[PDB]
Length: 240
Length: 240
Image 1 (cartoon, rainbow over the protein chains, first blue to last red):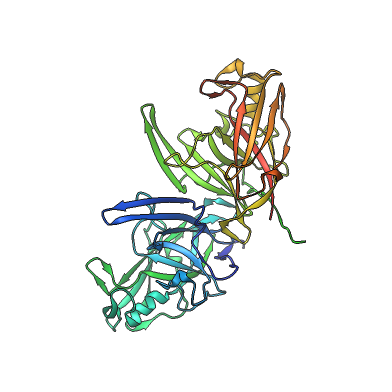
Image 2: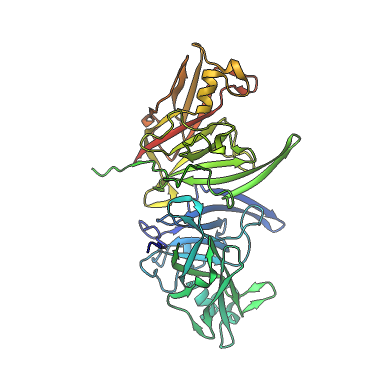
């Protein structure tokens, strides 16, 4: 047999970083103005150390964007990076080492014209300049401190009615690239909030060149979920 | 000593390719319409196998754009890729193997708003998501069949007055990323047209996170050079 298996391999960072790609020289940037303000955005296509995995990373005036991916090993309780919103893993490290991926999946689009969806994509081992369909074995997910804490203690913007009771749940849906297949997973069921790394089998997605993500909470108001739609992932394992 | 030296390492291709990155799923795309037509563009940031080097690649309705980089090992006299314009190296292969870089440097800008310059850039060895300043030792350049043939036999659009005499010359200028330094090199002097790989020492550029390029020919008309502004490069050697 010569089926090859490829596992996400994140960079090892000098000290404690939130990596949203180069901010001085981003791949792209733009501004949006509305009646409520003008906001500046920067976009970088992040890649892992192996060159197999790529991730869409939007950042803005206000930090990590709502539909974006970034890498971190920030364990230091005080990066000012997480002063406002603690996107770090509740597990405090990755599955196999200290770096993991933070993910925003609020459901807004990215790109100057809001027409692109934030995604992870897979490249050919022999040519990083071509996407390739793989069988996705799965990946590990866990909660962010930000979301865990909202569901446990109402520490977010809306306060006390964020707190999960036994009717509640927080569901991650993982899609294939064109979204014709998905797998559902729970980050929280009732008052049981995931605080470990959890493997999600994604083999039922079939061959695909990438992954997209959605979040649903039972705590919501008219405009969206009260639960922050940030989580973490690691260990994406694909096979050709 | 632990100064590290990094040399461009291009992908090895299955058979004979012109690689302008994924055309079905490009990093970006846009359209421009004017009074003369509407043209579609695709952009990919190419990276080498080592992950140290990145290249801006614009392609369009009409193929390889005028200010762009692409990779090729196409030796086969008939890729239809080179039917119209033969961007291949006059040397027919790279310095150390069959792949090399084809370069358009007409001086137009890229990006939906024509505000970005096509460039090569350097990333940190430990983190492909950060640009890093390096000392650039140099690289090899040579002519494209397209330009060589124009200068030798007037086989381009304008025909016979493309042919170089002893007053003529074709000069490549290599700049550092912010263009505050450059090095000049000749692809042709008089009727002597470069047909080998030629090393250009770029140490005088100082530390830089990338490279840009211009071409000047003594054969020109009111609107630009008659000599096609395409050439080839290989073997970029940088040091930190």
